[PDB]
Length: 178
Image 1 (cartoon, rainbow, N blue to C red):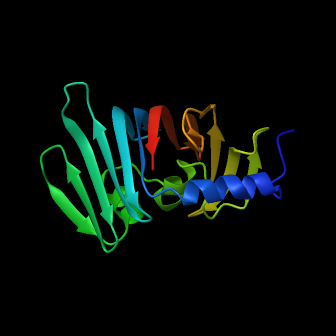
Image 2: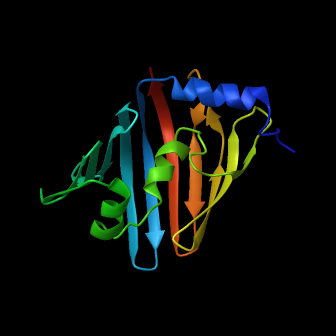
């Protein structure tokens, strides 16, 4: 049955997450679509409200992709060192890598926050459990597995999101927050 979104504990959990100044996680990344299959280790570091770096690496240790976002300056770097710049991370990853994603929202979802989503459920611990979000004529479903309760506040330990044609799976080995 989970818990009600109107619960003070939910609002407090969101506040505790938003009050953090830095977030860092790493783990297994899986992206699958009818035109691509990407498996890699990921590293996510967010040092500002809208400042973050996503790094995807292969077993070789080689860099598959780098997405470094700063307000007014998002840079995408591919394995060949080719650099591209834009003012929107979602638009760039959507038309540059072949991996379209509601990234502007995912950046909040990965922290256990709903972002612009208004259709969601919470688990028994007042933490985000499922999200239904529409954009670009598609409907995304986000599902959360267990949370990492070794940090304060607790952060998502695993999640999956899909809109049918695209599926992204993330498994976090750990988190560091401050």
